[PDB]
Image (tube, grey):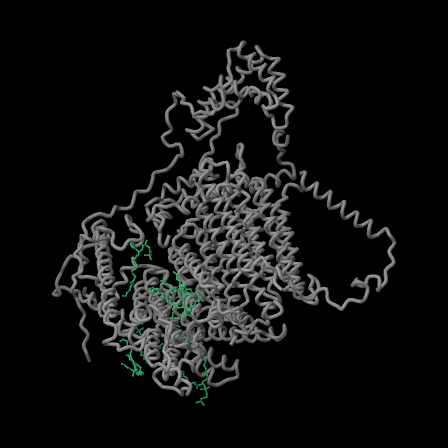
Amino acid sequence: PFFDVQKRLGLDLDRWMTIQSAEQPHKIPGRCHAFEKEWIECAHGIGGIRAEKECKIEFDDFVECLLRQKTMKRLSAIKRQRDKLIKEGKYTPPPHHLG
Amino acid sequence: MMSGRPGRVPLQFLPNEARSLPPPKLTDPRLVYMGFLGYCSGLIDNAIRRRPVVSAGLHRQLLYVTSFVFFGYYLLKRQDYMYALRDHDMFAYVKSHPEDFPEKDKKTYGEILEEFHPVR
Amino acid sequence: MNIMLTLLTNVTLASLLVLIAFWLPQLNAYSEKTSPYECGFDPMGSARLPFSMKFFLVAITFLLFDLEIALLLPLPWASQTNNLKTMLTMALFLLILLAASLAYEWTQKGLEWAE
Amino acid sequence: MTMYIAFILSTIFVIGFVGFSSKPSPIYGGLGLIVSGGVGCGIVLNFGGSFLGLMVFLIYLGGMLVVFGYTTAMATEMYPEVWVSNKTVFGAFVSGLMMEFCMVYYALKEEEVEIIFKFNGLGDWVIYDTGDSGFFSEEAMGIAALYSYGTWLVIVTGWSLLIGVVVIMEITRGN
Amino acid sequence: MNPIIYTTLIMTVMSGTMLVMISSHWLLIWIGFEMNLLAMIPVLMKNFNPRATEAATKYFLTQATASMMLMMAIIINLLYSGQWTITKMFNPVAMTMMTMALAMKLGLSPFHFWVPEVTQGISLQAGLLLLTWQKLAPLSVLCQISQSINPNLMLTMAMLSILIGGWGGLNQTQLRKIMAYSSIAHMGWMTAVLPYNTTMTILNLLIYITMTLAMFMLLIHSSATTTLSLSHTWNKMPVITSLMMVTLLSMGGLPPLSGFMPKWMIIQEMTKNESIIMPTLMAMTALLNLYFYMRLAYSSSLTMFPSTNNMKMKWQFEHTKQMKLLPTMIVLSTLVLPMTPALSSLN
Amino acid sequence: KTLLHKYSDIPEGTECHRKAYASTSIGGATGLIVSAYSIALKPPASFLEGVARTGRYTFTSAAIGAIFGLTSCISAQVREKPDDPLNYFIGGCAGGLTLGARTRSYGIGAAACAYMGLTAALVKMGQLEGWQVFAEPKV
Amino acid sequence: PGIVELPTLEDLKVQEVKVSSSVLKAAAHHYGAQCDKPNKEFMLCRWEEKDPRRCLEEGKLVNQCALDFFRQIKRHCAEPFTEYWTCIDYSGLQLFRHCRKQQAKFDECVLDKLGWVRPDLGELSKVTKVKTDRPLPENPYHSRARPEPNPEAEGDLKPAKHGSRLFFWTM
Amino acid sequence: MPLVYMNIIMAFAIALAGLLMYRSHLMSSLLCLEGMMLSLFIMSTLIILNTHFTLANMMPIILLVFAACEAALGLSLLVMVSNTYGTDYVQNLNLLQC
């Protein structure tokens, strides 16, 4: 904050909603609580300029968990190649994969 | 530069540590000049209200200079503390990084090849 | 599965009933039959010119009033929390502010229609 | 097919957006926003959220009704326009519809469009998460925490609404 | 307007600005922006003339567009990062979109045609308020997120603000319009110094705030809105025009007046950042601002103009509005240069 | 930026045709930008005269960039002085006179000679030195 | 980049207890009372290790104990349990409210046939302490080494050397 | 970076383009503004529902809260332009040009 009155008075007004790893109602975890927790605990007090270089793979894992297409691109190409080669009879799905 | 220094507590003029520094002298030329701005503000105030700018409202002018000097003192103490902090962070970083602050193998002008330009 | 199947059933039944209503009765239409109705005599001519609405203030503050009920509606689930004191204070805060808004409008003409 | 559902509803959302973004008569623009809001509520419903979609529904119908009531009162004309009446509104509608047509065309075949952001369009079912909500809907406990956690939001929203009524009073005073 | 209602609306504007400058959550900063926008329109509509309605409209729809754009940026940032904290933008598109989203609020880019219009339409007091208080919030947001700006975009914005403001100010005789263009030029200066050291931005903002306050309240106390009316003030009241010309010389930035200290310090900073063409460019093109400053000063105090006979009664009657803080404002507006290093207090 | 980079890839003087094309494209891009702003702020009257306005602006700008490019490459190649700042100076008067000859004015292109040629010399000097108009925050 | 290690199909070949949700709901309280140790151990493993690919053996043992419980209830109180779970299954929401007489028959049957008593209200929701013998996962999140903290700022402060050092201002 | 996000972002883009272009009326621009708001709500709701950011589901509600307030203020502005102008068109709103 520009003029951080909250730390001066020790009063919480918006810090509860800033991050996904905060105390959620009924202790409902976030989808990416673990990754956000690891990334935040990584770059705390270290500096917002050292965070990019030092805590990089933590933030990369967190942003993946948020959006997930180093995993969904994997799936898309898997499905594309499957539908490709099944067309002319190279592969047939196993019975458990269609019923 | 220093808004992100560790240990800073927001919204307070002097962060307690500054009392370890020599307080600015009451005679300080910066302080008295800021008192002069107090006198000047009185002169416009009387002039702005069609008043005997020199003699009118001695109390009003006296309040103006007194108010400027008080805020002048605290600003000067705040001003000096930051400059002291700048030097503190400087030299501490200098000592903490000897490799990035090389020393120079001192030699005299008798061995420096300084080219001479004939002034024609 | 169920909800859009329902919605489709209603809309197609309605569109059908419209179709039988509009194609079966063997209409015979002429110009004076479709002429606009103005209690007999021919209309002065308008039906799209600006029509003054004096509750424009009332109409617009309805928008804010109905907006607040969005904040209000989570109450049935908000009551079942472990901080009933804060929830009660905040709910009464919303209701008191709505009362203050309504009272300010009432006193400063507001709800009274323009003339 | 029922495979996408969200895709088709998003296309109807965009088409409704084109309808009122083409600057038609404000009643027709209101109708276009109405269908867009309904299908958007449908999208939010299909994405595991019930309260939010119905809230959009109710609030936007209230707002658009008041927009109509003002439109036929203040912002009307002796000759209301249609999406086909004027050539300008027709041009805007045509531009929007053919545009979104070619965007979705480039989208659903290649499914790797870069436009602004990298858009790998395999299927919206993919991104869903395998989770367990127990005996409480996550969205219900989420918007129910406003009165328990977000007290500051309560205060600022109430103050903004009251002063919004005050300004709606002052602006419309007219001397 | 009932005085209590006006007081509440002013308090809401100030509370929105404070919410912008104290909140960490992006949504709360937007809420402060929204409260500011909501409470600003009636202040303009206070006098209730068709000019006021025109200006209040043009103010509204521009600010609404900017705030919706700011939401698009916030939502993109949340999507790509999952954070509401005001630290830095993790998506380049989001920030290179919010840069102009926060720009129309300042009115420096080609997103500036609204500023002279609203300034001229609305009354002079609300004009002071718009040109002074309504710039701390977006500038505060820019200061907080300055760590991750695309310098090319921000510098281009600053250059265009300076150039078009200085040029447009050359071709208006209405005081409100040339003050709007001067505000655009000062926006350009501060926004140019923004990416390198925000402390100099704060110092320039403070100097501009106090000095524009002094200029505008001098205008109010002179009850002048056109160049001829201001020129006529010499017969009725000469000290106002005498202070007018000194404050205008400070507007242009001629040292040893106060107005130089930002223009000076800014130049000292970016030349430390290997930027040499830019400071020279701004230093030369501030002369366009200076030209109409001297044009205004010439026909206000330096040359007494044909007056009106009825002013014989005007001299007979004194003023009633006190114009609080004016004599102090002039003092910080002209002579604070010897206390220049006090800018370290901001840092 | 890549469109500007086209000029950077081609060494000054040599490959005069490619450099001329790149400079013409720079000019044309600036031309449609200026014409778009012109028809935005200043209202036109119809489609065909709007095309007339934007075509006039893009024609002037494309001619300016083209002749600048041609003069630069042929001057650097003929004199074998690629680092020569005056190589761009002929692009100034070429940029000057024809611009005046685009507006059918004498003094316009006469002053445009000195102004545009001087700015061309300094921008070229930006290549010669390590000048940065948009310097990234370093200190 | 790495290996998504997955235990082969042989480890997760549990006996797969097969009773419907209504049957499970009917015996809920007594099962929770007389099967708490395997459930509690398995869940503490699940929460601590945070890796279902690791606590599979506890998942086996909990199913074994559940099948033992159901075998006992089959052997001793088949008829009252059958009627009780059928009456639970009739309800759409599977409420215990409508089915109280059959609950009484089932409770007395298991009380005088297997020595069981239903937990009182809230007894089945108290945090328990397990005496598991597995070690505590040192790095459950598999976190990498944390970056070193920035050099701490310390030392006495002296007046700035030669004042502000800003242009001609000596002091 | 998934697909539905593309459609909502594209809808917001066309609504931004529509707002930044006027044809005759003032109501139509306001409608385009509230369409921008609708796209923002749908996008944010999708984001937070997907991420299970339970404490953040109030954010679209606050969005709509200030949405309606701005719409109300804009249409009151239109009330005044109609009262002093008879109509609502923007091209005749030119009295401030000089």
Which one is nearer the viewer's eye here, E232 or F49? E232
Q: Is residue H58 left or right of residue F120?
A: right
Number of residue marks: 0
Question: Residue C3: where, in percent of width, then height?
Answer: 67, 40
Question: Residue C80: where, in percent of width, then height?
Answer: 50, 36
Which one is nearer the viewer's eye here, H85 or D138? H85
Residue C25 seen in the current view:
yes
Residue H83: which quarter of the image? bottom right
Question: Residue G126: where, in percent of width, then height?
Answer: 44, 24
Vertical position of residue A6 compared to residue E189: above or below: above
Residue D104 seen in the current view:
no
Q: Determine the residue positioned at 46% across, 80% down.
A: F96
Which one is nearer the viewer's eye here, B23 or F33? B23
Question: Residue E252: where, in percent of width, then height?
Answer: 35, 74
Q: Is residue E34 left or right of residue E251?
A: right
Vertical position of residue F87 compared to residue A65: above or below: below
Q: Is residue E266 left or right of residue H26?
A: left
Vertical position of residue B119 compared to residue G63: above or below: below
Which of the image's four quarters has the C terminus of chain F?
bottom left
